[PDB]
Each structure stands twice: as C-alpha cells, then as structure tokens.
Length: 185
Ligand SMILES: [Zn+2]
Ligand SMILES: [Zn+2]
Image (cartoon, helix red, strand yellow):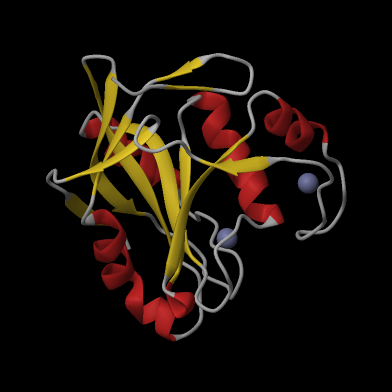
C-alpha cells in the first residue's frame, strides 16, 4: 500500500501510533503544563513484520524548564526498556505556550534518536494553540547539518532546510491500538 522514503531514497518502515497517545500524554503531564514547564515522554514499542508498533509511552525522570525538558536519569529509563524489551521509536514533548515547531534544542535532541533509528519521530504538542505535529530531520541533509553544527548557546538558528513533517500514513499511521503509559517519575 503506502510507503515512504528519506530524502536520500532510503525506505522507512511504518510506525503505528495509537490515536489515544497524544491526548493521554497531555493528561499525564498536565500538572507541568499548568505551570508552563515542558515535559517529554518516550515512544517505545516493538518491531513486528517489518513495521514498528508504539506500545508504551514512558515518562522518564527529567528536569523541566519553560523551554527545555532533558532526561536526568537515563539509567532507570534504559533499565526499564531493556527489562520489557522495548525499542526507542521517538519522543513526544509539550510547548505549554509556544506554537508547534522544532526548537534548536529539539533538533539537536532528535538527531540522537534518528541516528539510531532512521524512522525515529518527534511529536510536538502545543496545547495552548490546540495544535500538534510529527517531525523528523531531513535525511541525510538535516542530520548532517545538526552534526556539523558547533554554534554556542542553547537556542541558535540553523540555516537551510533541516526538518520536515513526517509522511502520514506512510511513515506514521495513527490507528486504534492499545496503549500503556509508564510514569517513571
Ligand atoms: Zn520543543
Ligand atoms: Zn545547532
């Protein structure tokens, strides 16, 4: 049926995303969102028949600021994913007041994810705007730009095209599948 390719023609395996995930994520992190602090969650799941299924939304230990949400204990996160045989398929986070886009920090963060899994996605929720989007870096050009970037500062510009909205339903398909949420906090 429908399938996708990176900018360099590499095929992307489909990621099945439970439709309930976005709302459920906002619910679970609402106390932070109410204080205008970002929160992230990890999109975890399994590979079955050449497709990925997101099965678990994992909220890791993290430190929340108004415009960043870095993980503060990778150990407990990775220990959990290993125990339950969960692959990292991407991540989701909030912009409590801003619009839906990928920030400078978001692009640098996502580079790690997409380096390990070509299909890796970044879901950005902008609840004060009631918008959301699902993004990835251009591959190879965007990953290259981010890897070569040595600009100081958390929030610096990047020139050229760096990222794009993902292909739906080819790359990412939202379906009625089950979801388990794990709060490690
Ligand atoms: Zn962001
Ligand atoms: Zn940069």
